[PDB]
Image: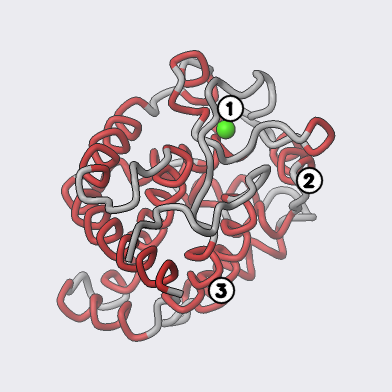
Amino acid sequence: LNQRRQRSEFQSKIKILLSTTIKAKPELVPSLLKLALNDAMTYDKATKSGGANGSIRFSSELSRAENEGLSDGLSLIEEVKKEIDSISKGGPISYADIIQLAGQSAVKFTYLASAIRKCGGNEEKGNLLYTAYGSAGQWGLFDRNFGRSDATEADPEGRVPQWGKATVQEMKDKFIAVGLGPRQLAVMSAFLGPDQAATEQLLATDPQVAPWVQKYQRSRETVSQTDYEVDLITAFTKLSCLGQQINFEAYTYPV
Ligand SMILES: [Ca+2]
């Protein structure tokens, strides 16, 4: 209870810091997305190893081809972690959490950009449109999965595609291997590359994924894009806590 509150007050502070930082550096949004994906996609059921554990901060993992071009995003993460650590009442925040939290703020940024765009670039109105729904209420479960532990080393090599050079079947296999499938692959378009339209053109060439891409394209044309937003959150939520046992009392302190 009191811990539920402490945690959420601590999340508010994190979120305002993330959105203002992302606001100063929007060209890193694709990096933050991919950083959250590539930290998570090492999860391997059989050996219960890998997953969303912050391993990706290790130079040994960061120099892997699949992780090319992610230095700048990881600097933003370090900078933001140092700032969050200085105001936390319940200890430093883990890398695994900040990486997934940077992901959430980047997602929100791409939703806000939609609203603004749908309003003839007018930024003041697009903010009101975005605020209207969210789907801020759909972040509920995601917001509860706060308290991930840090890995102390790189995740094993060889479990993450170089998305940019990958065929769609290498791509489906990655989602399948982690318990997902063609629908999650489609809705997580933005995570795969800096150019979602291009990513989605590639994805529509495989008939298993096609109907999902067309569905989400349709949803993104409606003003509210509710099904795109809700489904992304759902699958991202599953992805961000894989291999992780959440400490529901993390970031707690005397009342
Ligand atoms: Ca990892």
- Amino acid type of the residue tagged 2 in the rendering: Ile
Quarter of the figure with residue 27: top left
Say which element carries label 3. Answer: helix
Q: At 17% from the left edge and 72% from the top edge, which residue is drawn?
A: 123
Residue 197 appears in the figure = no
Q: Position of residue 35 (x, y in %)?
A: 46, 37
Residues 31 and 213: in front is: 31
Q: Is residue 198 left or right of 78 when viewed as pictured? A: right
Q: Please say if 159 is above or below 212.
A: above
Mark 1 surroundings within 10 Å by alpha-carbon count, few (fewer than 14), some (14 through 19), many (20 or more): some
- Amino acid type of the residue tagged 3 in the rendering: Arg
Residue occupied by mark 3: 218
Assign ligand 1 to one image quadrant.
top right
- Amino acid type of the residue tagged 1 in the rendering: Gln
Q: Position of residue 13 (x, y in %)?
A: 25, 60
Q: At 22% from the left edge and 54% from the top edge, which residue is drawn?
A: 17
Q: Please say if 251 is above or below 61.
A: below
Residue 207 appears in the figure = yes
